[PDB]
Amino acid sequence: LTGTGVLTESNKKFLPFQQFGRDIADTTDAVRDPQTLEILDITPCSFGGV
Amino acid sequence: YTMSLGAENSVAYSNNSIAIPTNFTISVTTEILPVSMTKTSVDCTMYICGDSTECSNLLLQYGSFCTQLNRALTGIAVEQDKNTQEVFAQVKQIYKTPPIKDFGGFNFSQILPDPSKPSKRSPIEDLLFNKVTKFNGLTVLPPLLTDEMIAQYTSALLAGTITSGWTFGAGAALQIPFPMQMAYRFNGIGVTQNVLYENQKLIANQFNSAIGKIQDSLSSTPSPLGKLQDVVNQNAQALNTLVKQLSSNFGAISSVLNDILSRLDPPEAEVQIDRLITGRLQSLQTYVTQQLIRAAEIRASANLAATKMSECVLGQSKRVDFCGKGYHLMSFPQSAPHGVVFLHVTYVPAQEKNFTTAPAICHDGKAHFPREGVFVSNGTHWFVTQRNFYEPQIITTDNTFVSGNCDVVIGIVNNTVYDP
Amino acid sequence: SPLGKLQDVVNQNAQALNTLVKQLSSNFGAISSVLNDILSRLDPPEAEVQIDRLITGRLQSLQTYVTQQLIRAAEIRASANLAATKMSECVLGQSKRVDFCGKGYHLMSFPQSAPHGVVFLHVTYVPAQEKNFTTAPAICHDGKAHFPREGVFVSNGTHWFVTQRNFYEPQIITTDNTFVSGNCDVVIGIVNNTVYDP
Amino acid sequence: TRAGCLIGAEHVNNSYECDIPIGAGICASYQTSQSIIAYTMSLGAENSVAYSNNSIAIPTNFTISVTTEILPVSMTKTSVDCTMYICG
Amino acid sequence: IKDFGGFNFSQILPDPSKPSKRSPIEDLLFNKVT
């Protein structure tokens, strides 16, 4: 699963079948690392109008 | 049930009978008007093609759709600030109320700005503000004028109205005592100034109680601010629908562009990307068109609000129901989130007594008609009183002009006209 | 710059037409914008599919133009309705509405023809030089309160006069100038002064 | 600023009438050495009317004022034949 | 009693005899629209 975003520690727990978490727009809000069973929040990189 | 249209009343109509009010009620009513909406900027490229060069290159083939969509949203955003300036920035000078709040018993503390609170916002405005309640290229632009700045405009308009009445709107602000200004409002709606001076304490108490009822009602319930919350809900729902549309596949293998790129070669991916682009572009076009229609409705509301500021706050209006129900006296503006709340002060006739009325009075073979007012009979005597308030006076040559003769008028009554 | 609103309307219409014409250079996912190139270089079924992509894009562009023109038309119609209302209420008559026909008290308005618009020359009366005066709501003369039929009581500090509100024209307080209501006790701020009888 | 990060403008404590609108009560102007300055917008000159229980101001003169209101009435009437536009 | 000093409002006032409590002018207006 490919995305560009900042990775941070995630408070929310994931059930074992629920490897990935999806938001309303179908973007992947949180992921669980394969090797280490920890949940990582994905926050999109900062963007704004100029 | 069949809906009732209201209580049935039969007026006691009669050629000889008039009803004259012997009392009045000072009424303050609230009119809530939407002024502006949240300024939303959507970047089409980010929404349709987030961080994908291939999708962006395909989007270029469509051409100018992004430029016109961004231009339309930017025009709406500029329009919202223009709407706010038109409603609240009418007066260049920032008027301030005198430090001693002596206005002949009239108390404006609830509408006037409260110093103790950190915001220089009125108590009623603080209630109003309490009562109103992403990463896809969607941004919210802050309004040019802050809420504090809007409160300063409403404060300046309120200070101008109390100190100068209607003069500051027309030109240079001319100080007038509020009692004299209130009498001018009475002489506008046809009631004599003397009646106001006789009942000035009663008018002050009724006005203060009416403001108290407005603030108590605002504290009790939040239904009044529902139109201002309706605008917010409509914009929020439209934005939510736009974000939800991203999850739609639109006939593609997946709604996620990254998945399509990852699992498919670029020409094969391009086939599916085109379906996704068509769906997202249609969703954006629908949202922008709805925003433009909503913007036109909000602009019409703002134009009406600016007109009401000019014709109710800045001046006394003779237009029926434009500035509250009843005979308009004055209006006070209160800032509200993305809107203006108008407190309309009106004179309402309260207690009515039936009398006997004659169009003219025949005295010396010549018909007499009132210069102002109407002829009323208590059943034993004939008097002339002003139409709005019952103030019977001895019929006199000064009171009544003379026209023609007794024969022509229908319903003329023989009575004596005193000569001073 | 004053005619900028009329020039904004002309500029918006010109820009919309230019954008519509420019959209004919957009492939819309087809091999080429030119229909003839597609027909010449492709077999008729393949050409029809590319032409369908071009037609879909061109139709969407035209519909966008028409919808924008309808929204612009509604805004222009509201402006024209306002202009018609001003023609009736400012040129055709004197208006008591505040700020509808100029700033200040409206006297008369003159219409001037403009390209795709109208220019209203509003003539207003603006008060200029104000003098502070002492004032009282009523004047007590013979134990009866006197109020001014028109005007307001003004004091120069030594004498009391009645003047019309908008323009300063001090006049001797008289029975013709002032009507009488009740007695002196009821009114608050009433000042003792003489009401002359002709 | 609430609008966002601003680069190339020097903040000035003094408040002036809005020239270019940044947003959130902040405006930018080119002022006299010349530099762009970011400032809180002034709402106008503060005026305290001399209100009293017994004081009135009456104008002793007048100015006849003529002001201009420009209103759009019509737009150019354009007909597009769709068949010609879509198909050459 | 419809006595208004010679002013007659019968055309604009509702007509009882007809089943709809509608004025004669309003009945013409309803007929005109198609």
Image: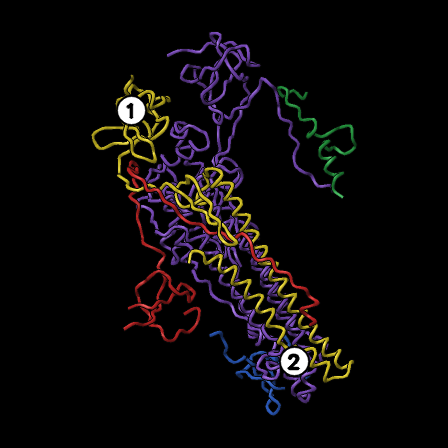
Chain colours: A blue, B purple, C yellow, D red, E green
**Quadrant location of residue B283?**
bottom right
Residue at 51%, 52% (x, y): give it. C117
Q: Secondary structure at mark 2?
A: loop
- When the figure is inspected, residue D64 is found, relative to residue B369, above or below; the finding is below
Task: List x then y, in percent, for residue B12.
Answer: 62, 23
Residue at 37%, 46% (x, y): give it. B159
- Which residue reaches farthest left? C158
* Residue annotated with mark 1: C173
**Split into 4 quadrants, where in the image is the N terminus of chain C?**
bottom left
Task: List x then y, in percent, for residue E22.
Answer: 73, 33
- When the figure is inspected, residue B51 is found, relative to residue B393, above or below; the finding is below
Instruction: Tell whether B323 sits left or right of B276.
Output: left
Q: Please, what is the three-letter code of the amino acid marked with disc 1?
A: Ile
Task: List x then y, in percent, for residue B149.
Answer: 40, 57
- When the figure is inspected, residue C76 is found, relative to residue C40, above or below; the finding is above
* Residue annotated with mark 2: B256
